[PDB]
Structures are given as structure tokens and as C-alpha cells.
Image (cartoon, rainbow, N blue to C red; front, top):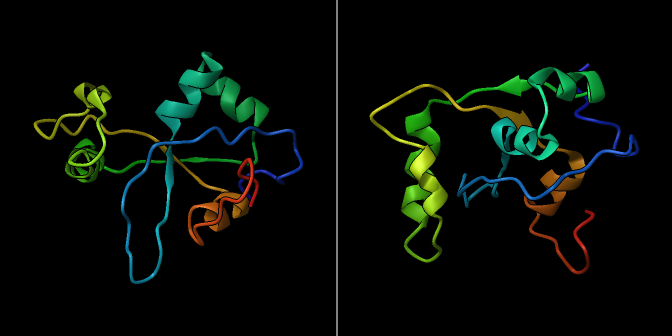
Length: 115
């Protein structure tokens, strides 16, 4: 089931890249599978073989780029070279955890982030 890990499955939520979602509701974070998978540095199958408790989704390239490129007025991320709105070769994203939805969503960080 889409439990997105059991937060107790020895499972690493290394700060994934996401952008302003909705400020009335609260910021969400879809974790670029391209980001996490580059972390493993292994095949896309190693992910699901290791964490079958998670699954992938995709927004259009033009989508993710749009938000990030706009947020790069304050911050700077040239890694944006990778993403391009003249292309929809899709990204990959994976659903963030309860920790993370609480972490980023409720905006809580008074330690080494852990909900």
C-alpha cells in the first residue's frame, strides 16, 4: 500500500527539491525521484526493491521548472539547467512522508528535522 515507508524502515528522507505549493493551506513537497534515486546512485529498481513502501509520480518538466525558476529570485539553483519548459520529458516524484508533510507542511524544524 502507498504508506510511503513506515518511518521506521531504516529509510532516508534526504532534503528533496520542491517549491511553493499553497500558502493558504500550507507548503507541500513532492520529492523528485530523480533526486532520491541519484542519491542511491543505482537503478530505479533498487529504489522499489529497497523501499516497496513508496511509489512514483510525475508532473511535467515545465511544471517543476516553473515554480523553482520563479523561487530563484531569492535563492540560486543553477542545477535548473536540467529542467526546461521547452520540454516535457517528465520528472519523477515520490510522495513525502508524515514526518515530512509535518516537517515541511506544518513548517517545523527545531532540531535535525524529524517531524
